[PDB]
Length: 237
Length: 300
Image: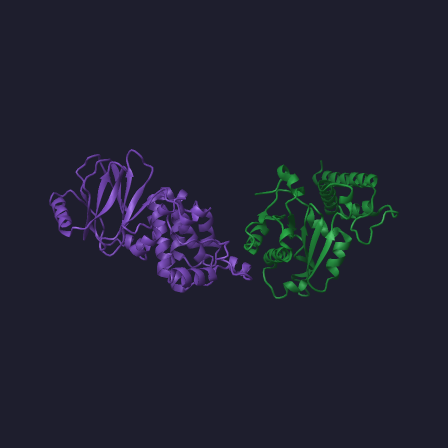
């Protein structure tokens, strides 16, 4: 069934699993027409498919051309996400195919179950976790490869950089969810915190800065503060 | 006009015949049911006074043989049996009739209710769903599970309804996942109508047989099969006009006959709200929507 706080350590066991987040698949800007009606213009999207154990991100870029002359786009987006995840799975060798796929939105269950009928042993699960994977487009290099894409593309990243050299997958996922929660709550402030010291750079092959263990504790502390302030503001408490 | 004689009534019992029922007292001189209309299937059904659990009964057609009921004190139920001796049977029936020991099938001449509930139901199809080939009649009870319920456990005592599963390789063509899930026309028309049932008459017969099992025995798997078969039509964009017109007529008489007080257990809120209000056929079931809205507005 559903993945919650109670079964949280299961994310870091040796059963291959993938989170699928479809939030950034169908992206639009809403604008006024010359006649003063409203109209949407789609921009490039992305499926956010993550192994939480390894940090291996499968970023399927959804180019605007996939929407051309299609109807009910927000429904189609769920199905197209399900098609692409099913295609990814089939493309992996048997021993790399997941034993579970956790969707971050319950509306993805039926599309994904139906696209995965050929895989009866892969469990499709919802989650009670409010995961901030929507903020993935606040990571500059991910945002950059999506917006530049001129055709459908799959780009492979490690969202944990080299962190698993020094910390466990539990701690790496905690760090990642904290950075993404910060970026989601106040993007400007989060990005300021991450780059305010110019001596700390992002390696060409990395997504986040090259922080020492001490510096990660300072950063993580600054991210917690950012999240609580914004909360106190939101709710006047 | 045909007859199902009873050898005796040794235990107090509520006896059902189609949509009618009679209380019989323990050792009452009851010797059966006469004037049973030829041309339809019938169901004789039982609910013991002492144990109001296990409703149970027999589907039969009088054209196929001479049938009687006899209590078995060992297995503790009213059993149907066939009498092969035509002259012994005629002589039993004439005696009980002369002594007026038989209730008359109480059909009102205006009243097409049974016809309307069993229009497509045929004994040959019931005997493929309920497999006991040595008998020309079929036993069903409250507790009998379906082939589909089993898969999710004694195969002999199962209800072999056609398995319908919206999230099955049967229901979904590879590369038509969204089309086939959101519009079940290919499942309905190619897989089920052309493929399995052969024609809408077999499909409607199973639908109507499933409802009657749900209504008369409170058989839960029967109710599930009845709703699945309604849902497959209503969830299909492409249905022959004649099938939609007939479905409206079928469903109207099922809703019309349902005991008012069992609507809560026999009707699936999600299926009915989806079929009448959300589905492709939301506007194709005028009679059904009007009786549902007038008789069970709570459910909707």
